[PDB]
Image (cartoon, rainbow, N blue to C red; front, side):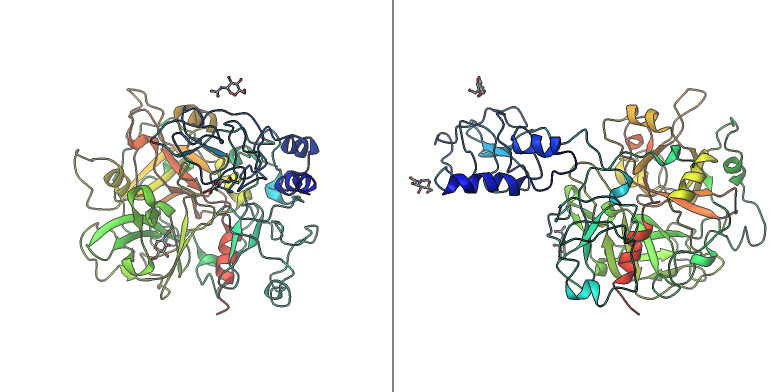
Length: 508
Ligand SMILES: *[C@@H]1O[C@H](CO)[C@@H](O)[C@H](O)[C@H]1NC(C)=O
Ligand SMILES: *[C@@H]1O[C@H](CO)[C@@H](O)[C@H](O)[C@H]1NC(C)=O
Ligand SMILES: *[C@@H]1O[C@H](CO)[C@@H](O)[C@H](O)[C@H]1NC(C)=O
């Protein structure tokens, strides 16, 4: 009979709520939403945007194609929000408003206060689907065992059926493999404990991370500039970085010295000839940029490998610099799997492989990427960063009706804003994966915030080992809109194990 099915239906629907079983409790009594909330049994009468829900048993204004006799499971009663068809938008309802057939409702999420520690390293739940709702493959399955033992894992981490787990110490969190090419994978959506890297505290010498084979060469020798560090010469404003605690005048953006930012990349549209975004160069072979530069639906954008070209070692915005710049095509583009623009530019990061490794010159050298430890260390001892670019951010996101785009790579140094100060400043929700930067607007402490290139680099130089580290990727920031506000930058310290898996889908 169905009554025994109903009991189990509830159970299977609440499968992802575990550690507190005062959370599994709160799930099963349907008053809040787990996952796509097919567990929801609450009494929210009202859609997310104000409207009264229609009665499930009504046919005015809308004649439902989902009724209690097609979905006898779902408790399609009165006019309460339910999710009878498993909408990836969660529990919904028909609208009493003749112009809107359906709208999602706004239902409290189950377990909200509960919080997962240590990036899912001790996760033992049964979550078996990534963030895009792509089902996990079993770890057991042929490829993941008898062929992927070379990349070994931590075995305090029990790999069980096809549940999201974090075996390889991934700073992004738990993950699992998915249907497609060999090695394909995704991140799963657990609710991680917010951990502000700036207030971490407790590196010795430099020690390398990926192989000179698949990540390519350059890692061993990153962050040192041919024309500066290697000639032991100092650049015109790096002193502000090392003396970042000193209350200085405010050195405005000026033209960069040649070779000053040799990891600077330009993402460039084939046709029409057009400067699209910025990016940085992290090996002979890989390029780091922001995901909105390739995929951003509100702007009806969706580039592929064949539409674009990078330009490396440029100094002049416009002139073709023939002795100097190498200008490469793309083999593959990797949007970060966690990337999401629907709420607000989360994990707005993208990796790009070059069809052919580029040769380091006086003007082409890779920047270093830091890990958690180092990133934290750097933020503890350094209070300003550097953003270099061709003012593409200002030219992309505002009318720029002012003076025009600069004609040479620009350098500027910007203060790093304290997390809470940055939180209050914006309507948008700054996760621990973002940081703000820019001067705190006084009239003797002015504001020109919207600096750099979209998806370009924000860097810091290490006072421990003299190398330059890339600490965030420029994204859109409120500072492009309102004179008082800050630049927004996507942290990079969590990326090593993701890059790792991306490079592992190769072999040669
Ligand atoms: C919401 O449903 C409950 C349950 O009967 C009722 O008391 C309340 O007045 C209803 N309001 C709307 C807008 O449906
Ligand atoms: C429920 O709606 C379907 C959808 O067309 C309709 O044909 C049917 O008459 C309804 N079910 C029952 C059992 O009356
Ligand atoms: C954008 O275009 C590519 C290539 O045609 C396509 O495969 C992909 O489905 C599109 N992107 C998204 C996010 O749907």
